[PDB]
Amino acid sequence: ELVRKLIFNPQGDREASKRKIIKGNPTNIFELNEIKYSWAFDLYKLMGFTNFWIPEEIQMLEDRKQYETVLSDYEKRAYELVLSFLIALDSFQVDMLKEFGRMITAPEVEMAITAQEFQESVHAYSYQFILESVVDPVKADEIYNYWREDERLLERNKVIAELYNEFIRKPNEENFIKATIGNYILESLYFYSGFAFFYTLGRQGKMRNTVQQIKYINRDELCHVTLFRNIINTLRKENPELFTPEIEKWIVEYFKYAVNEEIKWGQYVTQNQILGINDVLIERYIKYLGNLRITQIGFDPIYPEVTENPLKWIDEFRKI
Amino acid sequence: ELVRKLIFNPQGDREASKRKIIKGNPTNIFELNEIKYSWAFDLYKLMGFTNFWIPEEIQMLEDRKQYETVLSDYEKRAYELVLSFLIALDSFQVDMLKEFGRMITAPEVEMAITAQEFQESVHAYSYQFILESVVDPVKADEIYNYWREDERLLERNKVIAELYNEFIRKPNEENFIKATIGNYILESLYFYSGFAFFYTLGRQGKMRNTVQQIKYINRDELCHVTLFRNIINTLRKENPELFTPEIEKWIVEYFKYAVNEEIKWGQYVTQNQILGINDVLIERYIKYLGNLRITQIGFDPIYPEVTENPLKWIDEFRKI
Ligand SMILES: [Fe+3]
Ligand SMILES: [Fe+3]
Ligand SMILES: [Fe+3]
Ligand SMILES: [Fe+3]
Image (tube, rainbow over all chains, first blue to last red; front, side):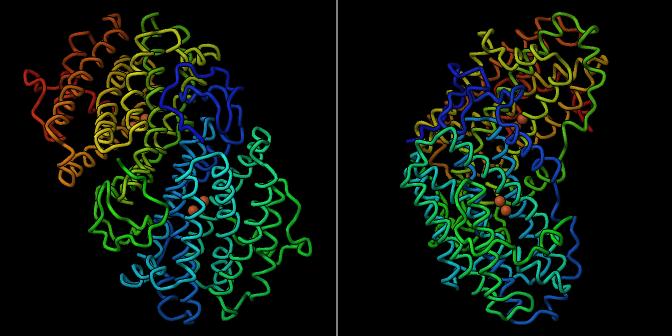
């Protein structure tokens, strides 16, 4: 039962070395002359200053043309579905990162979560820019609300929410580790179906404006995955009494499930009607990412049959 | 008793016009194609993009010299006291703005609070830069910890915390309005003693490096005061059943008290030993700011005898 740190604790540890990710005894003054988690502070500077960007300084002259005329009915359908879902995710993220930040006892980590929260706000801004630019008013509202029409979308949403609401409802150390694992999956996996879609269009000279935006969001997402990787790993060291077998189990299940559901989504969005990728490929990408992410947090691959990356080209395309 | 909005509400209002600052019924998807609070969204763009800045791109070559040799024992004392306190305030702010953000039901306002939270993180970074630059390692740790020595500082801190902890402990609509009023005072008042100090040094060519930093923090602070002014005013319209007489009373008391305690601080810091301002001036500044701020949230002046600004010159100096 995670007690939320009070605003000022005069009986708080002076030694940065005594800091913990959770359940530490801080003053809650940001004593940033001493850093225990150099990665937390490095990631703050990287997200907050180095990688700063302005959505509206990206030019949206073309895409509205290509949307208006050059895109197939299936290509427009995927565009709507992917943007609707990513809008939902980034919305959940700005809201939920405030729950993590208020529970974390290392100020440098709180700093890194604050910057991540701000990056999620900019993403929300970028999607609003993309739609204000690329499509008409009614279509933009419809895309924001596409869950109101599409039960596969509505369910993806309610499901992601559920895991976060457990921790909000019942803020215990188990529901914390579960929520944190949820965050890592959501940013590990659930963005890269969408990222892959847009980078396909972009390979063939389709929607290069949108794809610029996405390159920045994707640069930010890799920082976010790295932050939560370190938090989960540091959480394992500092709190092994939380990575019980029952949990280490529930992790690998959800991590497999999630790799599944991302594929059932990638396939619903596209339906092999998109010139550049197919239901087979989808499966080899998510399976690939999923292994990686789970191994990067100290677990055995969940799909050993996969070891190459189907789309190794992305790594070079998405670059800025 | 403010129930904290769940992460996704499929029974949430579609019409932006139905949004409320608190106790609204949102989906918690950031439907930013429709804005009800244009000021909230304007303030987000202003804080997040327009006014972006990097503390470390400000040059800190000189100040360490002027600190090392050119500053009186009283001038060094004020420097330590003011920086120690402002470090404490910005720390409280990054932490507490997460409590407001999670309670607010208008996404554009949540967006504006997220950006403010990020600006508070940058301030934390700026103070760490200032001390890493301007003073030696042991002195920097001592300044972060100056509350551990100085009971006037320790009490200022515990007092600000107290008001925030009430709302955290007992998150009801009264403790919400109290906490929110606390935020407005803290950013209205408690920064401008410090701001005034540093701008004095800076007038006489003392610590112009620090003073650059402060100009940026002060530009950010005016955005923050404006945000909470609008929130309190919009809260009055949307929730008059909260600005009871008992509250409207407790407001004017605290607002007067706070103008008092800022002066008892300004005077402890300086002690008329600082060439540029005196215990009399201090009193005419805080009394001036305090009236203004309380009138700007629809109240009668608390010090009518004051109507001019003692230090009208600041407005022009602090500019960038
Ligand atoms: Fe995002
Ligand atoms: Fe993210
Ligand atoms: Fe600040
Ligand atoms: Fe502020």
